[PDB]
Amino acid sequence: SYSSAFAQAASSSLATSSAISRAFASVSSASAASSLAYNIGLSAARSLGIASDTALAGALAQAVGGVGAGASASAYANAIARAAGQFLATQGVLNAVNASSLGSALANALSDSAANSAVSGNYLGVSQN
């Protein structure tokens, strides 16, 4: 079970990533959540070198939209890590060498992308207090 191992390491980092928890709590619509998962997924897919960034990010958009708004950071993180998990399994990137630890590597790419959402300085709800 390479997808479950990838999702264990990905979940370990996504659950310690308060920036990803804030990304999912900031949005209040399943299309805003799927669009965040698309934007952070295009960034992760470009950093990882994927030949179809729109298809991997599109699977992450459908993964987050599959639970919909008003859910745990674990539910969205597991949905992303299973959808990335299916994509990296069909690429053969998941292997007995370290399919587990590559889940932490994807969660680090998504964490860089969700911290990078603070570059735009408005999508995190915004405040002046």
Image: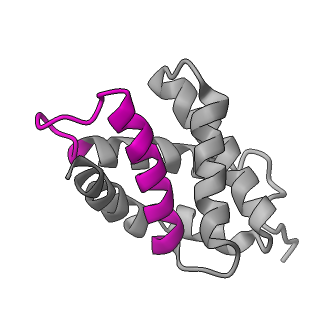
How many numbered discs?
0
* Figure check: 84 above or below 63: above
Q: Position of residue 28 (x, y in %)?
A: 78, 74
Q: Position of residue 110 (x, y in %)?
A: 51, 47
Q: Is residue 95 magenta?
A: yes
Q: Residue at x 73, y 45 (%)?
A: 119
| Foreground residue among 4 and 9 | 4
Q: Residue at x 80, y 58 (%)?
A: 123
* Figure check: 117 above or below 15: above
Point out the residue furthest to the right here.
Answer: 128
Q: Position of residue 21 (x, y in %)?
A: 55, 70
With 52 as the anchor, is 93 left or right in this view?
left
Q: Is residue 97 magenta?
A: yes
Q: Residue at x 53, y 79 (%)?
A: 72
Q: Which residues are magenta?
A: 74-101
Point out the residue furthest to the left here.
Answer: 97
Quadrant of the rendered image containing residue 38: top right
